[PDB]
Structures are given as structure tokens and as C-alpha cells.
Image (cartoon, rainbow, N blue to C red; front, side, top):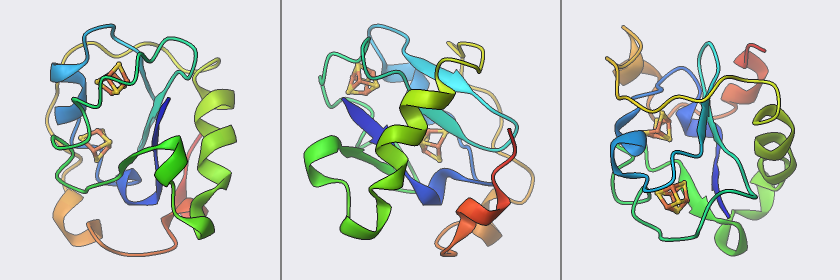
Length: 106
Ligand code: SF4
Ligand code: F3S
């Protein structure tokens, strides 16, 4: 499974979904998640994230291991997203800001 981490929050560019062959991205208010059981580890989404927020589980940074279980949990509750949409208005200002998990909305 590929996992979306911190920098996606409040950026949510959704470029990653255009490339997914199986459509396993699920949508929240200000973040996206990959459903771990449906992902086929094709790695096609990882170059597409402008925020460089997607990682293979085995390369998820040490301080971001919470995201592995979070993507799994939330993929079960959020709706599927299969088409790109515009970034959140302010995506650029928040791109690179650290600690954005405190801003996640369910
Ligand atoms: S690695 Fe492939 S199947 Fe998994 S979320 Fe990314 S694009 Fe979709
Ligand atoms: S910012 Fe998030 S919505 Fe996709 S393109 Fe990157 S993982």
C-alpha cells in the first residue's frame, strides 16, 4: 500500500487520483487517503503529488507512522474520489508546513 501523509492536509491537490488504475483514493474535507487493501502498489501516484505526500508503507518517515493506520481507518468512512478537482484555495501557503495533522477534519 501507498500511504498519503501530512503534507497533503490542507493542500489536497488531487492530481494523484488521475493516475490511479484502481481508484482507491477516498476523500475528506481537506485530505485524501489510499485504501490499503485495494491499492496495487503500482507507485504511479507518488510522482504526481505536488506536495510529495505519498509514500510506499515501507518508506513512510519514522515520525509519520500514524498515517499508515489513519489511511486505513479513514478509507472506510470517507467516499471514493475518482476525478481530479481544483486544489484547496490556499493549497500553496500550506504546502511544506509541518505538523498539519492537528488541522485534519473528519
Ligand atoms: S500505488 Fe497505484 S494503486 Fe496505489 S494509490 Fe497509488 S496509483 Fe493507486
Ligand atoms: S496533496 Fe493529497 S490529494 Fe493527492 S495530489 Fe497529493 S496526495
